[PDB]
């Protein structure tokens, strides 16, 4: 559950800020 669930729930901060950067 860490592909589309936690990936956008616990990474939303990075995805919107510095996903890979």
Image (cartoon, rainbow, N blue to C red):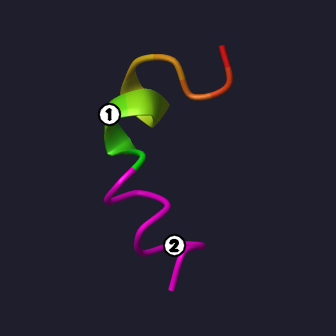
Residue at the (32%, 60%) spot, across then down: 9
Judging by the rendered image, the residue that carries numbered circle 1 is 13
**What range is drawn magenta here?**
1-10
Q: Indicate which label's residue lies in the foreground, 2 or 1.
A: 1
N-terminal-most mark, 2 or 1:
2
> Residue at the spot x=41%, y=68% of the render?
6
Q: Secondary structure at mark 1?
A: helix
Is 9 situated left or right of 7 in this image? left
Q: Is residue 19 above or below residue 8?
A: above
Q: Is residue 12 left or right of residue 2?
A: left
Left or right for 4, reference 3: left
Residue denoted by label 2: 4
Q: Point out residue 7 in the picture as x, y percentages from the top left corner.
A: 49, 61
Q: Quadrant of the C terminus?
A: top right
* Main secondary structure found in the magenta portion: loop
Q: Quadrant of residue 3?
A: bottom right
Residue 12 location, x and y as percent? 35, 43
Question: Is 10 located above or below residue 15 in the figure?
Answer: below
Within the magenta stretch, is there residue 5? yes
Q: Which mark is residue 2?
A: none
């Amino acid at each position: 559950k860490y592909e589309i669930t936690t990936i956008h729930n616990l990474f939303r901060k990075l995805t919107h800020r510095l996903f890979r950067r």
